[PDB]
Image 1 (tube, rainbow, N blue to C red):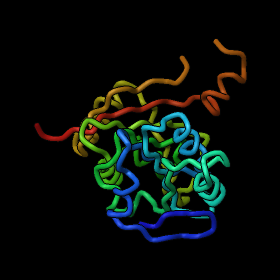
Image 2 (image 1 turned 180 degrees about the horizontal axis):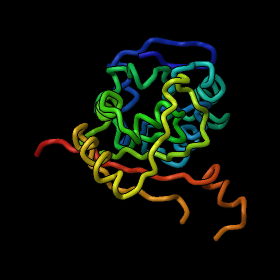
Image 3 (image 1 turned 90 degrees about the vertical axis):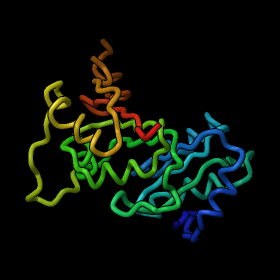
Length: 213
């Protein structure tokens, strides 16, 4: 596994990770974390939780990973970790660790993978989650469109029909049972909505990882 530490990228093993994991009751993984501030904040709010931000561009994470690696009084957060990788090749060292897996405003390709959906991606995310653990997605169509020009199909509205025919089976087919499908609002003034939605309509999707018994 590649870990980001300021401008440095260091190689870690499963063993290295487990040494850090010890002493933490929960594990959070944020996929497509960007600048990583969500993971940095989570680390502060939940000392019990080891918080891992993942992004395929190390440099996006330079600032936060350097800051989180300082002494606590200087802003260090030792239960924070930043890993460079994409959903298309997630590091094996992360398999089965997450209680909570977040996808916050994924770009169009990743958003597509979640709402069409796309089995290989769904299967890939499921590999990160412990049984009984949760996938939480904040979905918004104003994100950056990273898809090739030809792949710009129109994306579906997450209606009950869509959930029933497209998403539930496909998520069950990947090891996930969809819990929540809700519009994040549904009466602020014009912009309080957009601060807490960002921008217009964002929907929340949650699913529980299901295993044997």
